[PDB]
Amino acid sequence: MEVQLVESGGGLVQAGDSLRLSATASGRTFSRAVMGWFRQAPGKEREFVAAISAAPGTAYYAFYADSVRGRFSISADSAKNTVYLQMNSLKPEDTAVYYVAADLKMQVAAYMNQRSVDYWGQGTQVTVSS
Amino acid sequence: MEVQLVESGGGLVQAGDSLRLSATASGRTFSRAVMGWFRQAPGKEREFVAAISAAPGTAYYAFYADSVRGRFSISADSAKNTVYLQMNSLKPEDTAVYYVAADLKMQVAAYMNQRSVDYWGQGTQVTVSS
Image (cartoon, rainbow over all chains, first blue to last red; front, side, top):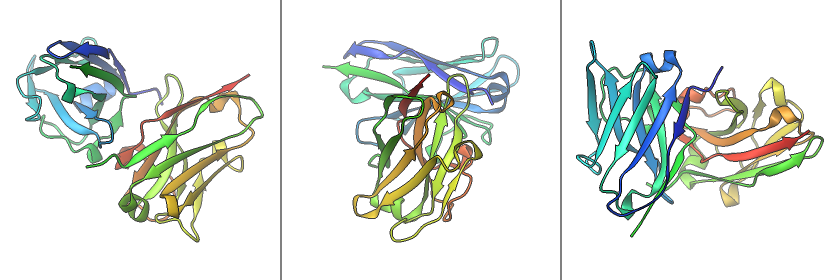
């Protein structure tokens, strides 16, 4: 089986800055799953960040965790089987390994429990210094 | 919630060589979950390597993927809440990011479906040189 999920982006930024993550999924996984982002801060379990689900036509439904609401924007492009996370007004508290996630059972973007995730990316470090 | 699983060890070895990896689990997960190891080779999805029965102290079952049978061995140290993956007679085809995993819905070592895994480690690169 070929790798389902591959993240790109990540790196070192300063407080206030923006950084974009993206991830590709195989066509089958992309079309069959609610796609999401998680983050694992130092010493902590991976926590839900945002999710996005396809709706009829060009439509998408998006759902964000309270901690990142407003500051982050999630999006997807089915022509490229890619999901994007644009992070803005980044703070030290946002420092983490960020993971893309796919849940094949969910149909509509909602809070995703990490324990229910079917496929994960390899993780990508984002560091925000004061 | 604290991180549940943390790998240690890894690197580059030569074909024919050996390497043991370790991972710490929280007290709760060590007691309650089947723990195991997966690996993700470049461009391939993560595949099952080995599993050990929940709460492995005095006695446990161990179970292995056919590809690593006899060469690989899994074990534990209950006193340090640690699981080990011993890899003998390493081959270039064993090159991968290796991940520890735990499944709270399993009690006896067995094939672990990546889709059912509750908690994941961060992964560690193991390269086997030709």
